[PDB]
Image (cartoon, rainbow, N blue to C red; front, side, top):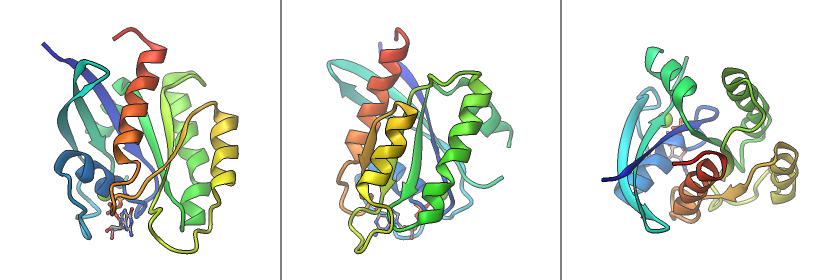
Length: 167
Ligand SMILES: Nc1nc2c(ncn2[C@@H]2O[C@H](COP(=O)(O)OP(=O)(O)O)[C@@H](O)[C@H]2O)c(=O)[nH]1
Ligand SMILES: [Mg+2]
């Protein structure tokens, strides 16, 4: 009685992959979550009248688990932090890896700019928009601290997966 959606959260160390994921599952902000825990979580959530069981891999480091989620994951959150220019620059590499594993430029994906609550961003919203536009994907700004944008990011990914394949 539910539809399963397999999601993978990727991006540089420190950007808030775990904090976003924990926020979605537990509705709290974690200051410090072991930066080495790579694991999968499950959330049941009704999105547009469909009961979804999200199977989410929170990636960490560099794994037999990750290989399978990369091959069989249906959508990707590609996360950078708006105060980490290098994490933004790194997106290209995460997107390239995903394209290669899928042999496709048409993979459900959302670009996520995290830590929107922090002052004096170094990556402007227009830089991120430019990048998401060239990739043909949505850009969503989040804060795992305030929860701004968190459900938006995950719901939008679910919708991008549907736009791409029957579920
Ligand atoms: N202020 C703020 N800090 C955050 C946010 N997201 C994560 N952090 C902090 O940034 C650090 C890295 O977060 P983490 O979730 O471990 O990153 P990961 O390596 O990508 O899983 C931790 O100290 C978090 O508390 C956010 O949206 N706002
Ligand atoms: Mg982590």
